[PDB]
Image (cartoon, rainbow, N blue to C red; front, top):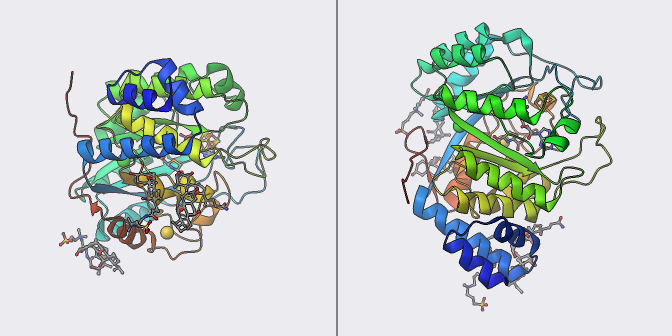
Length: 347
Ligand SMILES: C[C@H](CCC(=O)NCCC[N+](C)(C)CCCS(=O)(=O)[O-])[C@H]1CC[C@H]2[C@@H]3[C@H](O)C[C@@H]4C[C@H](O)CC[C@]4(C)[C@H]3C[C@H](O)[C@]12C
Ligand SMILES: C[C@H](CCC(=O)NCCC[N+](C)(C)CCCS(=O)(=O)[O-])[C@H]1CC[C@H]2[C@@H]3[C@H](O)C[C@@H]4C[C@H](O)CC[C@]4(C)[C@H]3C[C@H](O)[C@]12C
Ligand SMILES: Nc1ncnc2c1ncn2[C@@H]1O[C@H](CSCC[C@H](N)C(=O)O)[C@@H](O)[C@H]1O
Ligand SMILES: O=C(O)[C@@H]1CS[C@H](C(=O)O)N1
Ligand code: SF4
Ligand SMILES: [Cl-]
Ligand SMILES: [S]
């Protein structure tokens, strides 16, 4: 079908593989703009004008895994490794709550040191502050996930990365798509609000792969979906590969919103890294969440999944104020509660 016809099918929610492929393959400006408007309007209708702030503390860059894309991979010897103490992490969380954060995200490499009990202790302390806690710690045994839920954790982010099992295993040689999915299913069973999502523009990833990523997200009806471009890192095997395209990645965000109209979708830091102002554009094309960097110096600059990240030269407390200004200049509002998913049951 033509652009106008694909848009009509999207508006009528005829989400066939062919409609999603054609939406991702058409490069016409008018079509893309209309797709972006559609996603923006669906966002406003379902999740409103509140942009939810998730303050992220990247508390350790130690990792046991060796993912080919990631600057924290275990084989990268050209990176100073760091670990925040549990006291530092709690007090840094308390500062974010003082600054108005209503969710604290704890993210790390897969660092065995904390697992599971030091994380449980931290979570319990942060939960006393009356905020949501989200974990993004990678793949762990069911048992660990269960202990963290009992400790009070509310949400868990585990991007599925790529729904192509062959590409997944090549890029993540310690593990598999099956394992990743099983972790995601376990987290949902345990009562977490669960986040998935993928990178766009991975080496070897095709448009058909991106369609499969959308259908996977739609299948499992995730609470949150984190999408960004692949950004090559010079101390990795994928150093010389092409970066993911911003517009294609933005279309993935827009389609995610159309497919999952009541979901929580961030404007990721990676989007703001590859294009100046990329988060702001993404917030106008389907996204409704922002995750300001709350990692303190001198560690912030050592948490380099990809290079050139924005927010590295700012002061320790700048990023929450910075996103509150962004939200205002976008004519949006800050989140009034924890920003949990508010499901709209349909037919
Ligand atoms: C700001 C620019 C330039 C527009 C422009 O230059 N016009 C503004 C003022 C001109 N006036 C209206 C005052 C009168 C025109 C008389 S004049 O004499 O200037 O031609 C317009 C041009 C194309 C617009 C984007 C696309 O839609 C896609 C998408 C839709 C979403 O939903 C919201 C996000 C997004 C990215 C849009 C944002 C923004 O909105 C853009 C960049
Ligand atoms: C942390 C310190 C010291 C006092 C303190 O420890 N304050 C705890 C407040 C706890 N809460 C945020 C939950 C209050 C909600 C009140 S509210 O009426 O907003 O619901 C206080 C003193 C002045 C406060 C800033 C200014 O105000 C301007 C601005 C208002 C925004 O809005 C949030 C961001 C920002 C930058 C504020 C952040 C933080 O807060 C500051 C630095
Ligand atoms: N080079 C790169 N470009 C863009 N995103 C990257 C990247 N390297 C890693 N990421 C993204 O960063 C996310 C957080 S990684 C930290 C969390 C945890 N270890 C985990 O793997 O889940 C990953 O899910 C991945 O999608
Ligand atoms: O873009 C980034 O740098 C981060 C990586 S994970 C987080 C998300 O939850 O989407 N975004
Ligand atoms: S993506 Fe997560 S698990 Fe993979 S190397 Fe990076 S930090 Fe470790
Ligand atoms: Cl969250
Ligand atoms: S920041």
